[PDB]
Structures are given as C-alpha cells and as structure tokens.
Length: 133
Length: 134
Length: 6
Length: 6
Ligand SMILES: [Cl-]
Ligand SMILES: [Cl-]
Image (tube, rainbow over all chains, first blue to last red; front, top):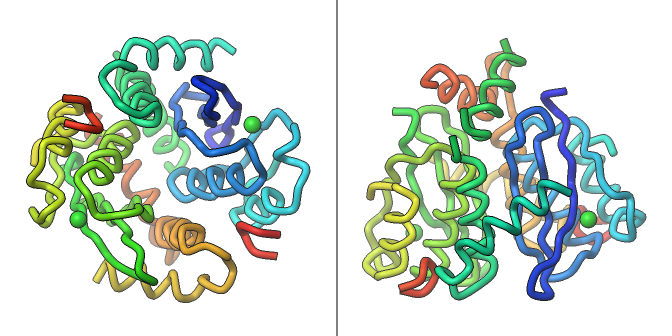
C-alpha cells in the first residue's frame, strides 16, 4: 500500500494538469503539462518514480495510456499499471491572482495542500519510513 | 539539519540543469530549465518546497538570485537563503535511451536516488531523516 | 509583485 | 523505442 499512487487529470484555463495522489497519505504531486499525450504522461511518471518508491499507479486508462511511450517508461521504472481535483482547483482559485502563470498557482496549491495541518507531507514520509523499517 | 538543501547548476548540450541536493541524505531533485533566470529558479524552488520540508537553501548566490522573483517565492514558502559530476556520469550512461535530454536527466535522478549497496538508497535516507525529525 | 514576476 | 518516444 505505501507504493500505491492514483494519477488523474484536471483542466483549468484550457490547460491540462496531471495530479498524482499517494493514496495512503493524500500527498500530491501536480503539474501543468502542454497536452494530455502519452509522451507527456510518461515523462511525469518517470519524474515521480525517481522521487518516491512508486510500485503501482492507478490511472484512468484513457487515450494517453494506450501507447508505447507510457508502457516503456513504466517498464523501465518498475511501475505496474473527484474531491481531490476539486480541492486542488479550490486552492488554485485562492492564489491565482498572486501569479502571472497558471503553473505557478498550481505549485502554490500543491504547497498549501501538502503542508496544511499532521500534514500530508508529514504522513507520506511516516508511512514510507515505517515501511522501510 | 533535515531542512537544508543545496542548489547548484550544471550544463550539458547547451542546456541548463538545476540540481537540489538534500545535504543530510544526498537525495536529489533535478530538472532541465530553459534559461538560468530568476523566474525559472523561483519556480524550481517553489516546486521543491511544496514536496519536502525545505527550511534553508544554500545557493551559489549568482545572477539568478539577485532579483525580486526568487526573493518573493522564497518569502512566500518560508525558505531562508562530486554531485554535478556524478549526475553527468549517469546521464551519459542513459543518454542514448532518450530522445530528449530532459528524459535522460530524470532517468539519472531515478538511478541516483534508488541505487543501493545493501546499505540504503538516498530516497530511503531522506524519508528516514525527515520521519525521525517529525 | 507576483510569485513569478516581481 | 526510447523512454520518451517509442
Ligand atoms: Cl490522465
Ligand atoms: Cl544556479
């Protein structure tokens, strides 16, 4: 269970945001990507998998998951294949006017989400540390 | 301290890579960015600070740190203001497996952070240090 | 002064 | 088949 993540997409201002939720803790990684393509999705996962011990990613199994590039990146990295989107959009709306670019506002929301008080950021480290022990 | 990170830059193929090292564990976060500018540097730090409990970030104090936008991002986030060679070595091992340098960098990050001798990896060490501190 | 353009 | 273009 420590290794399990849920990947979803959400849309604001005509841009695409990918959201990875560490299921056991509620910790999130999110970013704006230029299009909801295999290649962009593969790169996001590769990034994630380098930062956390990612065993299984549950996805929506849509168009950006049927292709060769996601499959190759997951293989390499050893990854097996609405409240949250709404929560994140809520926070984004609270900070939006503080940033020129949506991408900045997203990362401010990530910060807020993960550090709000334990925090999610505290919970993920606790769960992984207990697992390594 | 668990909260201390070192930020450096390195250059390959005409591109800029920013490397943040968690000093107590050797865990790294790295990204290709389009230019070594305040705005890009501020964004990278904002991103980092949302993912880990970042208290202090030691930087090279160069041109991309003298401006208004790193200072504003760091204020907001509450951050107070060998490895490059190692990372370029790993990038070279994987480079031909990727079209784009950015992908190779993230493969290198993965390798660096998950490599272990049997004892622990850097990814394991950072979690153990932050959890002990909580 | 925005977080990305001060 | 590259990790970013297979
Ligand atoms: Cl998706
Ligand atoms: Cl720098």
